[PDB]
Length: 260
Length: 260
Image (cartoon, rainbow over all chains, first blue to last red; front, side):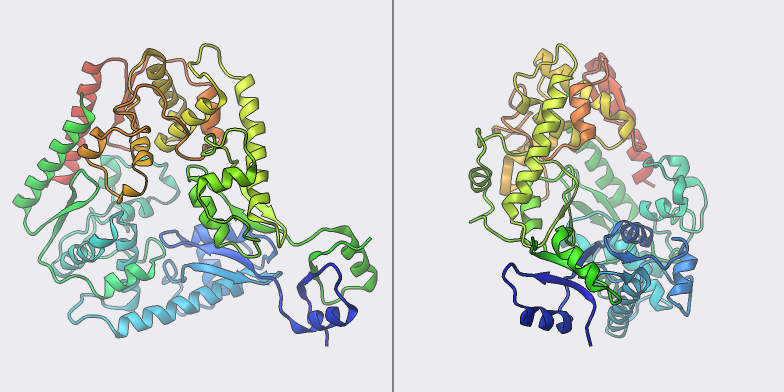
């Protein structure tokens, strides 16, 4: 009844202690930090490069991952993995580790969904995840998260295009080279929220618990616009004319800074 | 004859193999990714949270770390650590891992220094490291790295203030809330390159091999200015008139993007 694994051998260890250790099953555990804001394709490259991972995935395509995970909806994949420092034992498969990540996300989502605020325009749980991923990728201060959420949810409710750059970046796929021009924002893809109305078909990244909570409980504001203030915050507005003013304020601040 | 450590035992392992393993010293390796562009304080936090690290440092103050590593000049600390995925065996001390990181950087810096381009304005190796950390924190696109480097080194040579924001941030220390204003830019500190001429007294982050190379071999250009082009890249200039034009060009791009 010997339990295989990675064990710790002290200098003057006894035979008595060693047999106890080799049966205890108390293995050394390895870290895999799966960080919020990253994609599954990021997580899959980490798994390939991680020490002592049994590679049971034929390739790192998303559909293969949905196959191996036996997902009910294989289009509901991105954003459905809980971000954490995951502890694994040596020779654990990639699939079982992703399975643990998926099941933990499902639980957190279901709790967020059932506890969500009244009158949100999400049709399903994937849309809550999609919105959460949009909130996560919108680079802001922690204090402004609820308001950023509010703007996007308000827009989704009334039929205004979301116009968020990360969704455009996602929709380009491997054509994105680090640059984002005006032509890129103008080219229609299924994810481009400058061209499409509503949420994109799925999430764009892995949402943190911070974003998921903001998607489920946004601030109660009438805001429909935000722009950088030039410090490193944002000014929030309810109408186009106020917004356009706040845009001019931002450019003044930038001119005063970048020009000599 | 027997070497103590953390080893892995397969289910069908023979006693022949176990004997071989327990002498070999080929332990389980644990990963720690120390990323370029991060500070030593970021690495120190990572060591506090890393599994199976023996924590010997009294505190994570840089003077403590300098004393424990026994540096000749304790002021030459920031930036002097090689960024990589470092493999450590269990029960390795925090100090021993940092010592490995330091030594590898020293070797890399010495090699960069001796092979460097002629007529660069650096007095010592710490200045090369300081400049490299400045290039590291400013470079957003890899094809523009040697030209960013060129601008800063051009300025350093002729006595034009470097006016680089990450150094203002470093100089504020814990007073930096996450936001940077005009008041922050105009307040003198030892690191503030809007007020001081030349390099700050030490590096501001860990440079990668990319930035360290660019600090030793910048592109031969007449540029003294760069500004964002509005679409991911930068536009480089030799004079203030041309730069102020490029600033105006950038502000129009932001006007078209943000205002509706």
